Length: 257
Image 1: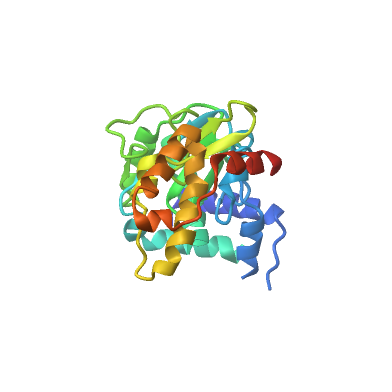
Image 2 (image 1 turned 90 degrees about the vertical axis):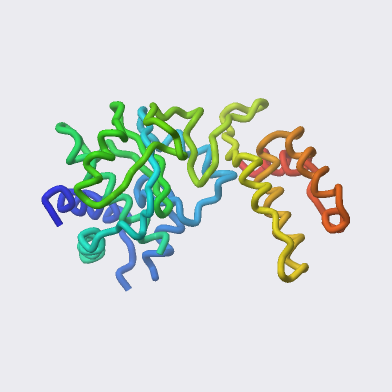
């Protein structure tokens, strides 16, 4: 645990401090109740609503990257660090990520003020920002000194600038609604959804499983959604399900804000 990790610890800790958490488990409830740039976690968030808030919590320049074997590569130094924070699973990997980003930032650039780092992590996945454009390609270099193997965001061939158009968090894109632009749709690619379809070893789970897939799919738009429902209804097992009409999912969503 070097000097950089120490400042990461002090800074991250001091932050979680403002939350005034109960020292008597209760850490999990604090995080679940406060998904954002203070916990620096999204664990327990609700995409359908949280997506409209994220753009406001972020600084101007986004930056993200992929981890290769995030858990396996986690050296003991980090846990030691995590302990120091606590002294001062998803919720923990998220806390570790918060330590990594800070550490690598302090090690890759001079003049970094962590109070201006706005990031939200969910395990190894993270959406980050800073007032100035930061290079994940340079952060990746510093990562080697810690056994971390960082690569472009979303299995990208090269390291390119992260924008609100190409950025993804929890595998979802950010797309403003066409009718009300300030309501941000969490958009999971249809491909990812199709590859999630399962005929449960217990047929009874099928309905609720597909329901949860529909709650993700309709965010790709009425045409894609109905195309999706048509596929499911092309065979008997899919025709036996009760699938939400696009119209109602969208309307309920608008009324939920």
